[PDB]
Image (spheres, rainbow, N blue to C red):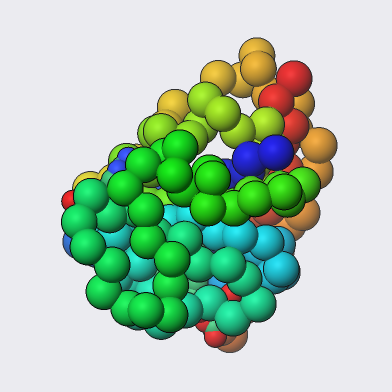
Length: 159
Ligand SMILES: NC(=O)c1ccc[n+]([C@@H]2O[C@H](COP(=O)([O-])OP(=O)(O)OC[C@H]3O[C@@H](n4cnc5c(N)ncnc54)[C@H](OP(=O)(O)O)[C@@H]3O)[C@@H](O)[C@H]2O)c1
Ligand SMILES: CN(Cc1cnc2nc(N)nc(N)c2n1)c1ccc(C(=O)N[C@@H](CCC(=O)O)C(=O)O)cc1
């Protein structure tokens, strides 16, 4: 299966500039926890913000254009991308916007990080529909020294 993995602020806001309007060392952690050892599909921009391969996982990129790091596998098609994975039990789609939009419909599970902050952003998340999904997990955490805001993880299976 396919899976989306994202961290949303308020209003489904996923980011500003080619950035994230927050800093949650904890999400990153949960993120890595959920991806380690799985192929991660991403988009030219998300990749540009990462800036280096992600250890422990097969980094697949989506660029209409030419690969520019020999360390990571590039693609020019959703189908390619998906091919580029192989015989794996779960493929992680890590964003950004356009990419989400695109894979949402093929996904069957979501790992969300609901951030409790109201910030202006230029990229929102695909509108999923409640009826379809069954929340199978929640976990809460209050803000702290390091994670300046509160958040709540969640995992939903497509009903
Ligand atoms: N908040 C989170 O949970 C989370 C997770 C990931 C990313 N993000 C964020 O999301 C915002 C940026 O996302 P975005 O939507 O602007 O960019 P993106 O999805 O990361 O990058 C899009 C690029 O994908 C390439 N592309 C997409 N689909 C393609 C296809 N089918 N075939 C070929 N190329 C394809 C195009 O590249 P070219 O034309 O240049 O090749 C396109 O410009 C950020 O601020 C970032 O931090 C957030
Ligand atoms: C900009 N970006 C995209 C990003 C960030 N947080 C997200 N958070 C969630 N839940 N989902 C995403 N798709 C997501 N994507 C990043 C940036 C850094 C790292 C990163 O460093 N990952 C290390 C984590 C520890 C660290 O940053 O030192 C890893 O080993 O997985 C990952 C994604």
